[PDB]
Image (cartoon, coloured by chain):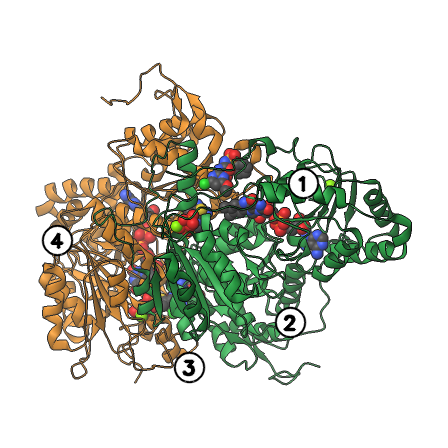
Chain colours: A green, B orange
Amino acid sequence: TFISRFAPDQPRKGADILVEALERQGVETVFAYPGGASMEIHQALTRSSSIRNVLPRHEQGGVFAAEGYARSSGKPGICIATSGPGATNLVSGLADALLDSVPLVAITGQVTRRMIGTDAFQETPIVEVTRSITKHNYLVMDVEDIPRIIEEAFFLATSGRPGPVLVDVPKDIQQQLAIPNWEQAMRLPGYMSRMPKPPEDSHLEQIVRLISESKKPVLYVGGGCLNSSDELGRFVELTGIPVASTLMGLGSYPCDDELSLHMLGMHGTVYANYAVEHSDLLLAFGVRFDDRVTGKLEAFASRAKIVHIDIDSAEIGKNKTPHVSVCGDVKLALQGMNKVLENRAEELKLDFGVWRNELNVQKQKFPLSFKTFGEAIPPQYAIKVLDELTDGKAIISTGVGQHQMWAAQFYNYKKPRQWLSSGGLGAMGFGLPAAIGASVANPDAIVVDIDGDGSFIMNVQELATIRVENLPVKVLLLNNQHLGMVMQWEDRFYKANRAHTFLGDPAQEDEIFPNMLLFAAACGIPAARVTKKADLREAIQTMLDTPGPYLLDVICPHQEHVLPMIPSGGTFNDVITEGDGR
Amino acid sequence: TFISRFAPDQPRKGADILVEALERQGVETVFAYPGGASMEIHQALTRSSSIRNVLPRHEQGGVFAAEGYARSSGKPGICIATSGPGATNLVSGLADALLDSVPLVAITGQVTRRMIGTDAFQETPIVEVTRSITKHNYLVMDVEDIPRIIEEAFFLATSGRPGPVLVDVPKDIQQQLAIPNWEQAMRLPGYMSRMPKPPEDSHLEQIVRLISESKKPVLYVGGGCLNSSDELGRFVELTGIPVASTLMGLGSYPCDDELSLHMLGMHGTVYANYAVEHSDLLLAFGVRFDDRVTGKLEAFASRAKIVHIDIDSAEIGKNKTPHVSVCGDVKLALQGMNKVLENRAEELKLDFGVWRNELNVQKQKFPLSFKTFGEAIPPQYAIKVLDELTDGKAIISTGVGQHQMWAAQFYNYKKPRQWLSSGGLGAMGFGLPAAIGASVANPDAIVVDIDGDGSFIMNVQELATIRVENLPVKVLLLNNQHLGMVMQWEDRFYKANRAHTFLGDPAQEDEIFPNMLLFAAACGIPAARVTKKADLREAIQTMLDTPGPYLLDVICPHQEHVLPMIPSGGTFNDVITEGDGR
Ligand SMILES: Cc1cc2nc3c(=O)[nH]c(=O)nc-3n(C[C@H](O)[C@H](O)[C@H](O)COP(=O)(O)OP(=O)(O)OC[C@H]3O[C@@H](n4cnc5c(N)ncnc54)[C@H](O)[C@@H]3O)c2cc1C
Ligand SMILES: Cc1cc2nc3c(=O)[nH]c(=O)nc-3n(C[C@H](O)[C@H](O)[C@H](O)COP(=O)(O)OP(=O)(O)OC[C@H]3O[C@@H](n4cnc5c(N)ncnc54)[C@H](O)[C@@H]3O)c2cc1C
Ligand SMILES: CCOC(=O)c1ccccc1S(=O)(=O)NC(=O)Nc1nc(Cl)cc(OC)n1
Ligand SMILES: CCOC(=O)c1ccccc1S(=O)(=O)NC(=O)Nc1nc(Cl)cc(OC)n1
Ligand SMILES: C/C(NCc1cnc(C)nc1N)=C(/S)CCOP(=O)([O-])OP(=O)([O-])O
Ligand SMILES: C/C(NCc1cnc(C)nc1N)=C(/S)CCOP(=O)([O-])OP(=O)([O-])O
Ligand SMILES: [Mg+2]
Ligand SMILES: [Mg+2]
Ligand SMILES: [Mg+2]
Ligand SMILES: [Mg+2]
Ligand SMILES: [Mg+2]
């Protein structure tokens, strides 16, 4: 039973209705940056005792923080911005949350209704702008629609395939007094009828049937399984099928397990891509068959019966035509198949040890390899040390680039929602604010931002947010003085011709630039730089043991390449297993 | 006669056609940030000897730099970004350039044509997103359309009412070889027929007629006069009409002149708003009648014959219905009226000294006033010192907030395109990157960023750009530890209830946070902080005399308010002339 701060017959500002609507949704944390068109909302936020605001230094940092809050908890992330430039600064985050299916609710202020369309001060048609990069958006035209729209927004952002929902609120609606009707019925008749049903036993038994008939089965696990950790693990015990995970599904099945094929795809392991290439049954659970994973669609699992389970009917058969499909919650589908596999255990006699050995041979012959050059710190080894000293229990957020892939390869995530990384959009500057949101969602957790010197500096202003909010955010900065991922493609396909990929100072060419330690110093964050590989273990240990925020500038040779690499649009026979920029 | 780097019969990559298309447009500087979908363009940029790339650290910094390049030169600014997150990071700049009518050409990379619509890697419908916040945009579907689209883009961005034009280029189009046809005809038949004609002598003589019949004429000069500096000055000699300028038109008529009413509007001087309130002839040249200037439209120039000259027919009569209108270039309209006023000089006998004295009385009774508290540095006085030591010849870019208004009030700009500030959108984080673009456009000029501690930190990452590019950018940081403009509205209309407007550290409440000097130190920029008013003159002099970049942290008491202030939607009789937050 909810307790309001106002009488049931007492009129209150629309902004106070908006905030209370968040309270009834269980919202404890918001990332709001104030502005002229949203001052009423910020005033109403101070009157709330249950909602905490984490003030960022940039609205892109605010929405990225809401993402980290969401990806690392399963809750929806809530960011609030003002009209005009405040709203447009959320755009990268909205498109990011859409492509990665992150539950997110963005509230933007707006000019008064009579000023809309008149090119008013700090006015942009944010609804018209964001319609193609959100799951849905609203323009509140009456104060009485606030309780219904906010309920629909949270329902749409979290149910089905999650995504971002933007709610544009004009200033006059925030000031207008009203008595909210919390018993309103949502106007989502078509969307709720389109919601998938629990999976039938008919479809589930045909899948278990195909599992017994198969001799080379591979699990293709993606971001749709982040809530099916236990159900997937139980499913693997009953089948023994190896698990190949995507960049988004990392942690769903423990990466340190003997049945784990780790990540597959363009920068996936050689054995994971081998398993899918030579499989006869591909169990695609919670994936969307991205070109980063498949490459050439005709050659991806070219001799496999493809079972695809997805809660979005639009994804089933979009890129890869499956044999058997199940449109519904993969969590329920695993529960139904676990009871079938458990009762009919002795009837099926499932044993794929021959197929597993065929893959375990590939593990030994083509594992994840990195080269150590003298005393220079290899970034892969730096991440592996972070895995050890944290026991694989840390929440890892990353930027985008070489360091993002190495954080995916050389860290063994044991649970889902430990791995926070922009996959679909691939937005740099994501790691640091996402670490902020993850730490507020998980205060007693180890949050480490494995960032790159290009990505880190983009939203470096959020270091101020980390200190002011006193968040124990660790920044493992893998500094290579380059836009490494773009530099790697320059070495491979453009004869190492540098096209504006060096981030340092050409005058002082051998000096590390900028001095990221002084960025942390400016915001009162203790920092340190480690260059020699011997000091690396003690440096990372100091970062973890030192309470509060900490930045560790880990210098790395820039000639490193992410391996292995399947070129874009290529097949498994085009995999690059060796080579760098030397 | 243009000289190509390729034979007229030699095939070349579409990216090389794109870059050469820029060369034929006279483009010398671009602000490009590389990414996977635009690597071909960046490779083609290195082959160009005439086009320089200024690599920012954030694409929002890139587009804002293109704005400063444009507003401070009259040329179009050119920014280039990759697909997905690179493109979405341009959004705030595009909407900014649209509302302020800044000539700007944005080029975004895109996934290959066959991948569009498939939710591909780093794909966003940037054309669908930006259609409502650009003058026009394109999606290049064939390599042969590049020479025509780039020509149309620059023509649309610069002709008529300027604005931003985005050109989305897929990756396969950049790689495809072709022989460009530079003699292509632009497909803009309706837009060119809609282009305004030179003004008729019929309309111009009726204006001069109304000038002689008027006894209280006021000039309402805005951003449309930035290229009519001489024509407007000559027009004032022949009429003697006082000049009230907008936030965008600052510098069109010298602010230090005896006929200058300085800025009018919400935060405009008392005498400028008085002149418009009690005028009988309002010569609105190059304005759009913003609510920041008019407030309540019915009371704005309620007893004045309104002559409106604008190159956009959509603006004539949108908010304020005029008596006489001229749809065309105000530069030509002034030339035509100057010949009429010069020949018929003795016939007209123009003398408004009675009206000028009525205003000069208001200048003495209600001037721009600031209060000095002990030794605390008043920001107004700090800007006035910058005016002295630079002789009013510096290029000033600002953020958005209290410091933006004080930079508009207490600096006497002598020429147009010295004042670079986000007016319509009002985007924070604009000053520092715009200063970058202005310095590259005007290397031998004094470029000073009068930024606020909130705005400055948003795009603080561009300090690295300033050092790497060795730009003599001065940063006059007016640090008040608050979001001052939002704080001012809290004091006036919300009983000084702080709603997330303090930017410092609440733990160390009296410590200046963050330490902006260390931000400059991180990027190898010499910096200094001045707190006592006595040291202010020497500190600013050191900033100017020290070659290269320099950051000056000017600490100011946060209780200052921007005065005078006409509340939003109010009239002249509601002007607030005194008060602060103490
Ligand atoms: C530089 C870079 C390199 C990359 N290279 C790789 C790579 O090598 N390998 C790789 O895997 N990724 C890579 N990516 C990321 C890639 O772009 C995609 O993010 C990823 O390939 C696709 O993730 P996904 O298949 O799990 O689908 P997601 O984006 O995670 O979407 C989840 C899917 O499952 C469905 N779903 C969601 N919830 C449920 C539910 N409860 N029940 C049932 N279904 C549900 C959804 O409808 C959706 O289709 C890279 C990214 C970057 C930036
Ligand atoms: C915090 C804040 C406070 C502000 N308060 C004020 C204030 O007090 N006073 C103020 O003035 N502004 C203020 N503004 C800015 C305000 O929002 C607008 O930018 C400004 O009021 C309008 O500028 P403008 O009238 O010159 O039109 P512009 O935006 O500069 O547009 C130029 C107009 O002239 C036309 N035009 C362009 N070129 C030509 C040409 N060659 N020939 C003929 N016509 C042409 C265009 O069609 C257009 O209509 C403030 C901004 C902020 C961020
Ligand atoms: C930025 C807010 O925009 C608006 O809401 C707005 C826009 C156009 C006309 C009237 C209003 S209003 O009268 O409904 N409200 C304001 O104008 N608020 C406002 N807040 C701040 Cl902090 C500053 C400002 O102008 C400088 N104006
Ligand atoms: C980010 C570029 O996006 C694309 O162009 C793209 C998208 C989807 C499918 C194929 C391509 S592609 O084969 O036409 N080109 C690439 O995929 N380029 C690319 N560049 C970098 Cl530097 C990295 C990368 O994947 C990590 N991919
Ligand atoms: C520029 C770019 N990609 C294009 C790009 C541009 N801008 C954004 C916001 N996102 C992306 N993905 C990359 S992956 C460079 C990464 O550089 P980094 O942050 O220092 O990481 P690393 O050097 O390990 O590759
Ligand atoms: C938050 C805000 N306005 C809302 C806002 C939010 N975000 C952006 C990008 N732009 C704007 N205009 C202002 S004007 C605060 C200005 O703070 P400042 O940069 O330190 O300048 P000052 O303190 O002098 O007002
Ligand atoms: Mg289908
Ligand atoms: Mg790097
Ligand atoms: Mg009209
Ligand atoms: Mg930034
Ligand atoms: Mg400030």
Kindly identify which numbered label has been placed on residue B497: 3
Can residue A53 be seen here?
yes
Kindly identify which numbered label has been placed on residue A275: 1
Amino acid at the residue labelled 1: Ala
Between residues B26 and A436, which one lies in front from this camera angle?
Answer: A436
B308 relative position to A416: left or right: left
Are the residues under marks 2 and 4 on the same chain? no
**Neighbour class for label 1 at 10 Å: few (<14), some, many (≥20)?**
many
Chain on which label 4 sits: B
| Mark 3–mark 4 distance (CA, rounded to whole Å) | 53 Å
Q: In this view, does B332 lie above or below B24?
A: below
| Mark 2–mark 1 distance (CA, rounded to whole Å) | 44 Å
Chain on which label 2 sits: A
Amino acid at the residue labelled 3: Asn
Residue A14 at x, y = what percent? Answer: 56, 73
Residue A145 at x, y = what percent? Answer: 63, 67
Asked whether mark 4 and ligand 2 are closer than 8 Å, the reply comes as no
Amino acid at the residue labelled 4: Leu
Amino acid at the residue labelled 2: Gln
Residue B275 at x, y = what percent? Answer: 23, 64
Q: Nearer the viewer, mark 1 or mark 4?
A: 1
